[PDB]
Length: 139
Ligand SMILES: NC(=O)[C@H]1CCCN(C(=O)Cc2cccc3sccc23)C1
Ligand SMILES: [Zn+2]
Image (cartoon, rainbow, N blue to C red):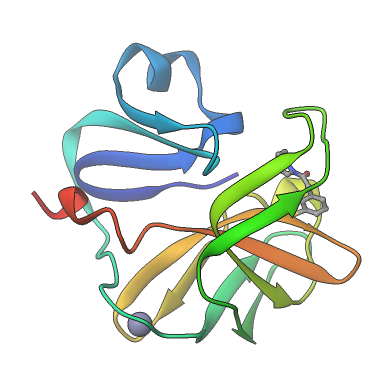
C-alpha cells in the first residue's frame, strides 16, 4: 500500500484504489496501473520533473529504503496477475531489487522529489509507475 498527496490529488496504484477513490475519480489509466482521485485537504508531496535514472525507494516487505538505478519509462510486458491479464504496461521503469505484492505503493524518490510508485516486480526486479510526465498534478 501507499499513495502520493499533491495539491488536491491523491495518486494510488489503480488496482488498490478504494470505493472513495472511484467515487472522487479524476483520471485512471489501466495501462499505467494509476488512478488519481480528488481530496479536500491539500497534499504536501512534490513531483520530480526530470530524467533522473537513480533514486531511493521504500520497500515495505523489508521495512527499508534501498538506492537503485532504474530504466527510462517504457512499454514493458507485465505477467498476468490476480488484478490484470498479461499486457504491456506503459510508463514503467525497472530496477534490480526486492519486491513482493504488498510493496505496491511504496514511493521512489530522487533529489527533485517523487518519481513514481512501486507497481510490478518478481524474479529479483522491481518496477515503478512513473508520474513525472503528469504535469497537471502541479495545478
Ligand atoms: N501493475 C501490475 O500489473 C500489478 C498488478 C497487481 C500487482 N502486481 C504484482 O503483484 C506483480 C508483482 C510480483 C512480485 C512482486 C511485486 S512488487 C509489485 C508488484 C509485484 C502487478
Ligand atoms: Zn530527478
